[PDB]
Length: 235
Image 1 (cartoon, helix red, strand yellow):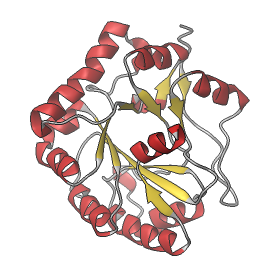
Image 2 (cartoon, rainbow, N blue to C red):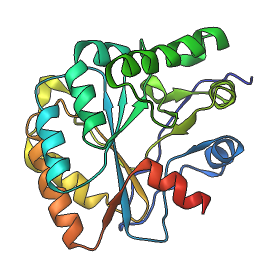
Image 3 (cartoon, helix red, strand yellow):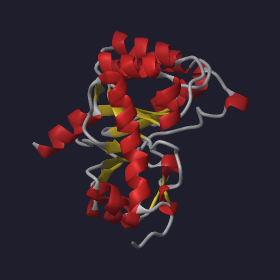
Image 4 (cartoon, one colour):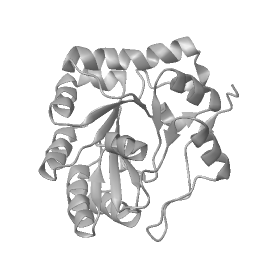
């Protein structure tokens, strides 16, 4: 502790400049193994995904990523892994990183270290049953909610907490706005070192991603993985 609830958030990117979470959050972030940006000194973008359930487009998103030769980092829940073992196997077989979004997607600030440990390990246990493998440990808190206690405890458990610097509403099933909506957000919020957080449940999201990668590459951006991000910063 302190175990005061905190929701990851920030004023969105403007002018294609990296957003800032605030002196307050930045401090807590650094204090532990957690980040929301990659290398802001180069024109690089890191794509990450939160996967809690499937709505039919993840296969196309994987096809798109393969086509553009980009490595995604998919933060999955226990329900997602159990409902979609084959997509999980594709993520692994196709070179992507599988991140941890906890088994039951609970608010971790309401959990004991003991519970936290089981919430995270059980996801890897299930992924391993499927893939026979295990990626470096990355955590994206369910609901984007954390606290100093959660950061400390998950860090003590070996996890690197990954937040984001680009996100928009591509998760409302009752109001799926379409291709343009998502594409424009991806183009407009683009900035050096950006860590995108995308979902794969909304209509035309794979097509929007396809176009955004084509156009962002044309703009001079290189897309790297979260492992790349970790290895490079460690250099």
